Amino acid sequence: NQGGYNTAGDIKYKTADGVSYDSLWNLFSNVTDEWNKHKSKMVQLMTFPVTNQT
Amino acid sequence: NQGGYNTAGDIKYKTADGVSYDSLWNLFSNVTDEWNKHKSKMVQLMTFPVTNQTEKVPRIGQFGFEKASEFGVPESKRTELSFYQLAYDFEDYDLAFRYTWKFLRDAPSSQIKAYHNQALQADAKLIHRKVMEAIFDNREREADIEGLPYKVYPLYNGDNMIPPEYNGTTFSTGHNHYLVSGGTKIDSADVEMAADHIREHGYTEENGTQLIAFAHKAEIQEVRRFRFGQTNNNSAVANYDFVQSQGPQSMWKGLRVKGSYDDVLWIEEPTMPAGYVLFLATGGTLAQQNLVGLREHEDAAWRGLRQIPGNQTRYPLIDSFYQRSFGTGIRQRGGAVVLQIKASGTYDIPTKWTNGGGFE
Amino acid sequence: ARYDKYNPYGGGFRAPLAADWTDADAGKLYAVGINNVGAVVKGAGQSGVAGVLVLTKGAKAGSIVDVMKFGEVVEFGPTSGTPGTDFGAAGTAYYADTSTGAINSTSGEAKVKVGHTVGAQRLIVAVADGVVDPSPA
């Protein structure tokens, strides 16, 4: 993993060959991984909410 | 400068006469001095607000014509466009006021208002230095725009950029606009040369323009001697007459005009280091905007002098910040000339205007 | 050099270029001929000198070029000169070296005449049928 503070210089253009860096990040703004949907299904069929701590 | 935290022990309450220091600090709360006003006035005449973070200066060639005939057709004509590219720089500058809790409890409120009014004076002093070093520091600089590097320029400086030819007067690599007088005092021959070094690029009185010169008073005591056909410094001769202003016009732009040599108006400039003069074009068809561009951030949230709330907040320590971010470059590299008055050799950057040598 | 007056009907012809011409040749004038495949080469091909050629930019092999036989060329100077500064002499005949296709004012028995100049910068192209002298003394 990449780590650390986000800095100016981790930003690398406003646009490149006419495409905008905001539009590129907007693609990933609301994605969800089908593996994380599967993992959430497996948790849902394999767990229960604890009401009684013992 | 003083620096450090403001502390109890920096506080003053009353004079031995019973007069409270908060009333003395109340004088400094709103005033601005004639020296910062004078520096602000040099900036206001010498600069323009930049709209494009980079400029292109384009040029095109010429066609001509031929004599006709009963038979036969003319030789074909075309022209090819070319340009030079000029960017403007940008940088951020920060200032802090820091207090102990007991200083803010016991210090006179007028001192805090004076510190705010002094931040406005420090901003004016910063912009003035950054405009002056754009002219007097004859080194090249680089700026990044859209993440792509561009050069930003002083006047012509012995560089590979070739001035555009004006009227069949035509130039080379290694042209220059920082000049060394070749003499320990100013000649009329230097003033004549420098004003022509502007006028060879255009910027003429036929082009509707006015020339101005800014000089320390020590060299104005030479210009007053320049009567037509009479010898002056270094055995040069005045090929025009000095004319004192009325009381040429008595005043220009609200500045104290001394007179004219050639048609160039002469102005006394106390900020100038003694061994130097600036010659500058104005008005007409070329000088519809001034020598130095001032660049500021694209977003209105980041323009101007701004206060940032600090990051030690209430007890036992308090701070706050002022920020301004801007930068400078020259568009009209031929629209002004810097003359240094020295006997021989290389041009010197004034220490007070070396880039990175200080601030404000 | 540049084409000033070109006539498509018998003043010049389309042909395919035999090899890449680089931007180092942009605005130079060369004499050219046709190789055994039917493509344009500098100097004489199998055809002898067929005409003269200027490209304003580099061009790829198998691209189509217009070779001039009769017409006017402006901004002219010898092939060895810098294009757009090193212009020709006025009033004088110009000859192609049949080996390199280089054009200059020096006559020689094995060379082909390509034209003559009307003032320093303007060449009247009218390429000869063959060499200046096919039977030296």
Image (cartoon, coloured by chain):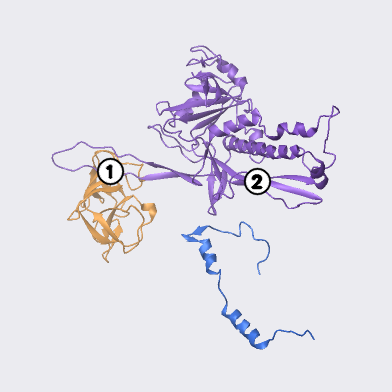
Residue C102: x %, y % from top left: 32, 50
- Residue placed furthest toward the bottom: A46
Q: Nearer the viewer, mark 1 or mark 2?
A: 2
Q: Which residue is mark 2?
A: B323
Q: Which residue is mark 1?
A: B77
At a point 53% along the width and 54% down the height, the residue shown is B146
Q: Is residue B145 left or right of residue B79?
A: right
Marks counted in the figure total: 2
Location of residue C108 in the rendering, given as x and y in whole percent from the top left corner: 26, 47
In this view of the protein, which residue sits in the foreground, B19 or B77?
B19
Label 2 marks a residue whose chain is: B
- Local packing at callout 2 (Cα closer than 10 Å; few below 14, some 14-19, many 20+) is some
Residue B181 seen in this snapshot = no
C11 vs C81, left or right, is left
Q: Quadrant of the C terminus of chain B?
A: top right
Q: For this rendering, which residue is in front, B323 or C92?
A: B323
Chain letter matching colour purple: B
Nearest to the observer: residue B347 or residue C76: B347
- Looking at marks 1 and 2 on the same chain, the residue that comes earlier in the sequence is marked by 1
Task: Tell me if mark 1 has few (under 14), some (14-19) or many (20+) residues whose alpha carbon lies within 10 angstroms of its own.
Answer: few
- When the figure is inspected, residue C132 is found, relative to residue B202, above or below; the finding is below
Which residue in the rendered view is the most extreme toward the front?
B18
Q: Secondary structure at mark 2?
A: strand
Mark 1 and mark 2: span between their CA atoms?
56 Å
Mark 1 residue type: Lys
- Of helix, strand and loop, which one carries label 1? loop
Mark 2 is on which residue type?
A: Gln
Q: Which chain is orange?
A: C
